[PDB]
Image 1 (cartoon, rainbow over the protein chains, first blue to last red):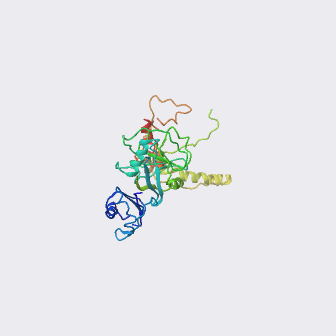
Image 2: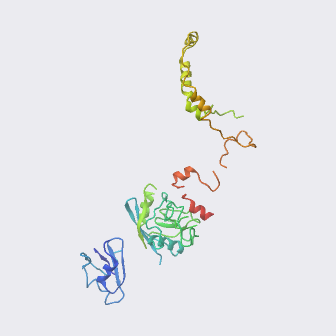
Image 3: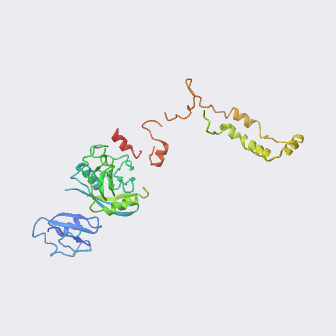
Length: 223
Length: 119
């Protein structure tokens, strides 16, 4: 119970969040108005009963040592349909089934390879079949490049697109990744399913309802 | 043995269509159709001026200066019941203009990564 649930502080930064908590070891602020600060020690982790409602850039930030403000990597991409946000798809990319495609989706969300889903759009979206995007080269599913080159093989097809928010590596799998909102067992054996959005399944359903008639692009994304 | 089809009669060349004999020829033919036969031998026994009478050097330049050489085929072409439809040799490994336009492929197809992955 060393992590906090500090909210009420997008204008804040990690240094401004950790300056009040300094010996904080972890400080990961969410894309919404929430952050979690964790101290390594035991006496320094009791900041909720010690510096609650602390002033963070002329704003009070109440700190509670809980997990109310919120392994397989989670590609958390605020997928925006058009100029408005269609929801934050926190697609838990299944590293237990397809770890290479899950790491490719997580790196495309985090934009650590120079290109990826942070800013790309899904130009191959079908109604309750597939929504394929992540290609940052041609922006149509006909470009894209994986970590091994332009084209990479699928890792494993142990998972299946059996429900909403299930993510697969679209194609042979380069930078193309497909989110599924329904059953896609007919395409099994060709696209390796590498995700299941426990959070952002409503965002995947909104992306499937919008898909393309609208520019469904995740401008903000990360791990 | 075609026996069940109908075809357009003719398409005039571009210099003949630029001179435009077809418009007043069709107007004269439709006026003749709306004429009665009583009016036909009435105009036979009393004729009138002005058939087309546009100029001469427009037709002269259409025949000589606006003359375009057509696409003559090879020495070894054999015509048959078909022999006017197999123009795809649509190259293999090459898309179409409609596939470039409707899928947003600039002169990057959306299936290019799948085609390169399949080899």
